Amino acid sequence: KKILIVDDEKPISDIIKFNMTKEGYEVVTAFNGREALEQFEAEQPDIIILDLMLPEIDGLEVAKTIRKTSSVPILMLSAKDSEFDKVIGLELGADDYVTKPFSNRELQARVKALLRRS
Image (cartoon, rainbow, N blue to C red; front, side, top):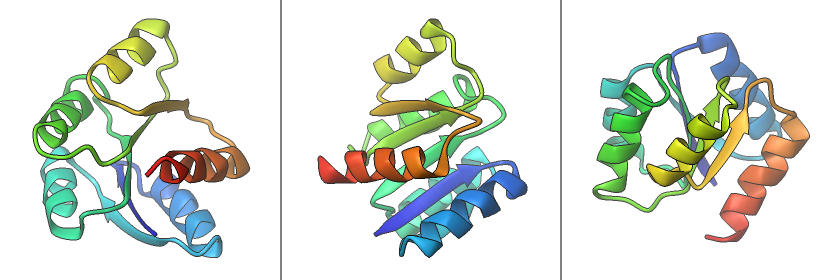
């Protein structure tokens, strides 16, 4: 199963990359909205973990732009855990919203849950 980890933070990207790889997932990474859309179009991941510096403005435009063409599960990973952020992320098309810091086992279960419904 392929996960595109759209993260502008390489350390977090490596953590998710390592755990998902240890679990058997192939990982592709993007570090900006341009790459995110580039990697999304180029790699077509089974699930996208969206974590950009601007979750709603950039990630939202990435999600908005991705949602214009794909229903690919988007697990909005964001440090922002407000209901507005949660609701807006979900209202904009995010299928799930996990807050950073996340549990590798839970993220693994949620990716699995997300993937389980796809």
